[PDB]
Image 1 (tube, helix red, strand yellow):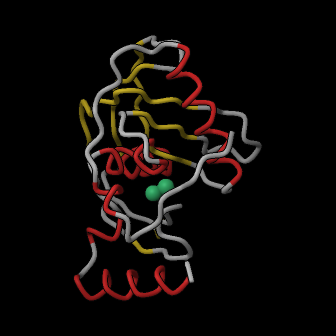
Image 2 (cartoon, helix red, strand yellow):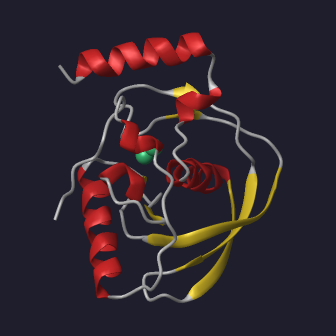
Image 3 (cartoon, rainbow, N blue to C red):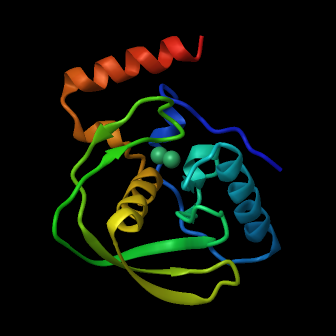
Length: 163
Ligand SMILES: [Co+2]
Ligand SMILES: [S]
């Protein structure tokens, strides 16, 4: 089913997720609900933290046709290099976008939806989305890289939006 996505200012967005202990049927349900939610919001990534589930689970699909499901359970950053940035959005910060510094390339290791370990080297948009989603799992939001004043204007506009 489609889950509720938390919006700033909600302190549960700052919670640090626990590792997943075993990828069982219940973990797979969460994964599937996460995709359903992400797609319904027209998103390209979602972290469990954003739907009040405090486990290290991320779903991503950067494809136009919404048929390239990437699941990152207990993701681990092995290496990163370069610098880049684009104007990022976030499902928990509606209608607000800002350029944020990110690594250009990342190499990560994670478990997939079957619990199988894999490694992934990503650049471009996918690398940026990976970093954005991993930030969520440690209670970090893209606005945290901006000036205290930008953060204020963003805080003020989301709060007025969710009227
Ligand atoms: Co986000
Ligand atoms: S997000």
